[PDB]
Length: 274
Ligand code: NA
Ligand code: NA
Image (cartoon, rainbow, N blue to C red; front, side, top):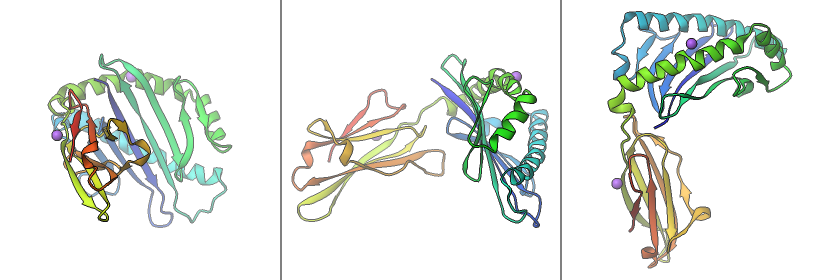
């Protein structure tokens, strides 16, 4: 029922080679819908989902200019940051930002987000109040003061409560056939002896969307929390996801074990066995 829009910006300096590279990607839930890359050839902003290709040239040009303005801003930021940390003019550095809005099933704002990081560590974050900042270190207190003076949080609040939510609603409607349809997992259980007295049971989930999923193993109905091995959820490359969970069991006791699969695309969870 609930949904999110999120942007992910990365700016990477390369002093003496060129201006910093700026790349942005945007998502609705777990679906990417846009990329901008200052280093790409032609064109620099590309659509990544079909429902976005429905938008017209005014929309595209508007977004393009926002990306171009941000790339310039990020160049100033990276310069300022090397000063803040008394760094050499020679090393490469990375500035990241992640922002967006979460809405409930009624399309109403649940909460907004904006966060930045420098060289992979938290730098400054908008608090959930959309009115104040958390500086992660002493240097980020510089930005905090500058942004307080500029009433930067007020601009964020206006965006997060307004256009962020409005546009997310629009994308969800235009993209409803995919964005609002959960694809349940395709499942199976496999068996792999590790010796003649123990064997691995592996419970698979393939082809599911969104990425959130819960795979568990039980022995006679008791959860095997501490003895289940999970791989990280991984992308299939076609917008769907994959995961597996494994337990190692005494040979000949396989019948005691059940795999349980919970996913938004499954009205009732699945129970699977070897
Ligand atoms: Na707004
Ligand atoms: Na299945």
